[PDB]
Length: 434
Length: 49
Ligand SMILES: *[C@@H]1O[C@H](CO)[C@@H](O)[C@H](O)[C@H]1NC(C)=O
Ligand SMILES: *[C@@H]1O[C@H](CO)[C@@H](O)[C@H](O)[C@H]1NC(C)=O
Image (tube, rainbow over the protein chains, first blue to last red):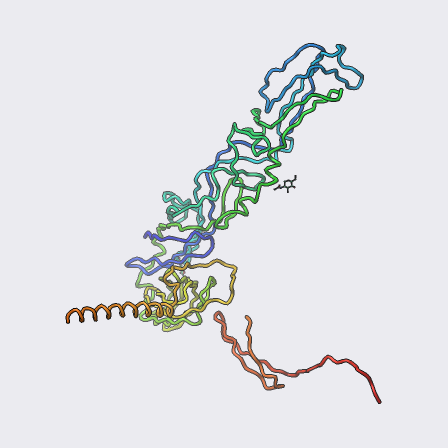
């Protein structure tokens, strides 16, 4: 017997329901989400880190004009200097007086510590959910994990679940993200093949050990002022360190709906934003005969000290007139009230107490005990505690949020004004008759 | 829970109250002033005999 419903997305906050076949007894149904991860399909453009800006040895020849071929190495900057006359230890290095040529070479390369201190640039497409459910139908615990696509049944021993598509997934990741050491940033990195000096992604490669390193650091070779054999060069600062200087806060601190970002794989676990349609096919082994279940001949309810809040605040007493011994579920058939308990053992002619949570100052909600429905009407007080450590289990519907007496005053003034208009118009009609 | 109430300053004479909570049962509250003392802040001006 399939049953369709819509569960809130929030992890925790167990969700109650009552399934009911025409010839079978009403049966408890529990749907609760223990985990929910958003795993998007991501591809990798480039890795980046500190460059080493290694400088090879000078190529000095003594009064012969030489030029350097354009090497394919990363950020290759090469220059020739005439009129040099080098000195390293041991005196002059060229015999020939004042026409010697020095060749200065410079190129960049990943630092030795780039295996840990590297940032990986990702493009993030649309994400899909993989939510874990616990189903407590017929006091039989069933833990499962299922995708939210509407086409994937959940692997269970005797249960079939379909998770309908999300109303609106919000995708916390932007189209371009950057991952550094488990910290995820929504950064608009430049495209591969586009580099700016002193900016993020100034040096790029397909992998950490890739040969095709590419960079456009603003490196310039200068003429050696002192008569030695050093290579004087200047270069713009690494954009990796300049990005770490003002990276801002990562996605683990700046993310909507309060869900935590994890890496390997990139995912956003325990997000709470929408609603999942659940089509669940309860096996018939849990459905029991209506004759076996003790029906309730008469039931009445009262509410004592209703405190409407996020906690299970509010107690209701049910006076039942059961016929035979057994146990059968309870349920609350209002969107504003959620009952704490699932089933109740009833022998005959007794009293039970139940706990519920509401977001409305008026408690006008129908309780179904074991098949039979009776409504309960009472008043609920606002809580004294301003801040509570657990989330609300019900949502305000904006019509039950207005209290019963405030509804009475507002409807009384509106009805008095409207009836005053009606009596004015009928006096007009009576006067026009004359 | 914080209960704010008003008790007479009579020694002895137990004072009754009810602590009603929306999430718990009402509780008996007894307040008895077993003793009091009104100690002034004094200074010695002089001593004579
Ligand atoms: C950047 O680094 C400098 C050090 O040169 C430091 O003074 C500064 O606070 C950092 N952050 C910003 C936002 O400039
Ligand atoms: C629910 O509990 C009852 C009594 O504890 C037990 O007999 C029954 O097997 C449980 N339900 C199912 C569907 O197994």
